Amino acid sequence: RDKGAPLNDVAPFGCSIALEPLRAENCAVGSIPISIDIPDAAFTRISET
Amino acid sequence: YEHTAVMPNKVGIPYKALVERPGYAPVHLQIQLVNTRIIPSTNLEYITC
Amino acid sequence: PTVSDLECKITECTYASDFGGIATVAYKSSKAGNCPIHSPSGVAVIKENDVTLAESGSFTFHFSTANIHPAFKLQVCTSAVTCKGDCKPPKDHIVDYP
């Protein structure tokens, strides 16, 4: 009510926050580059599609 | 085959990614970067209130 | 049969020294009956020693060639045909000699 910067409304990305050690929940970027090594068995076969 | 997928780390979006392959059939994923997690080591220095 | 107007084609798989290669085959012939099969010369072990043939039917067979992607010929008791497939093999290959 004599607030500085309310980071759950002004932390870049799209973040809103709870009580946190230093975490910014709910950010709308912060991109996690995921790379998967998928075994060929887990697929659907190309002749069964 | 080995399905890379980077998307914005955005909590509430099911981005429904695709393994492009011709050995086997392309198979759907959802690489949904749900909830921004950050969480480093911390130290409580002082409560204010 | 004279296995004429035949086709062996794409159906893909995962390829293994044993009998991992597969290829569906539109076996088409001018007679119907039994058919011993193997690639024109020794380059493959065919799981199915002999394959039945209808005239314009299709029967997938099993084989192993050596080729990871099996574009290996199959000499179907008069008439060779490429029994194509694009097959990515296992990641590991420590078990005894091919």
Image (cartoon, coloured by chain):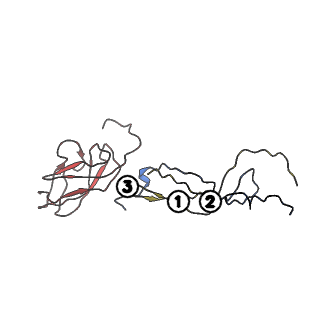
Question: Disc 2: which chain?
Answer: B
The colour with which the image depicts chain B is: yellow
Give the quadrant of the C terminus of chain A: bottom left
Dot 3: what SS?
Answer: loop
| Residue at numbered disc 3 | B22
Please report contact status of discs 3 and 2: CB closer than 8 Å, yes or no.
no
| Residue at numbered disc 2 | B10
Which residue corresponds to the image point at 41% horizontal and 40% vertical from the top-left? C92
Which percent across, then down, holds residue C51?
19, 54
Q: Gap between marks 3 and 1, in whole Å?
A: 19 Å
Which residue corresponds to the image point at 20% horizontal and 50% vertical from the top-left? C74
Which amino acid type is shown beneath numbered disc 2? Lys
Give the quadrant of the N terminus of chain A: bottom right
Which amino acid type is shown beneath numbered disc 1? Gln
| Residue at numbered disc 1 | B30
The colour with which the image depicts chain A is: blue
Which percent across, then down, holds residue B41?
72, 44
Which callout, 3 or 1, points at the residue further toward the start of the chain?
Answer: 3
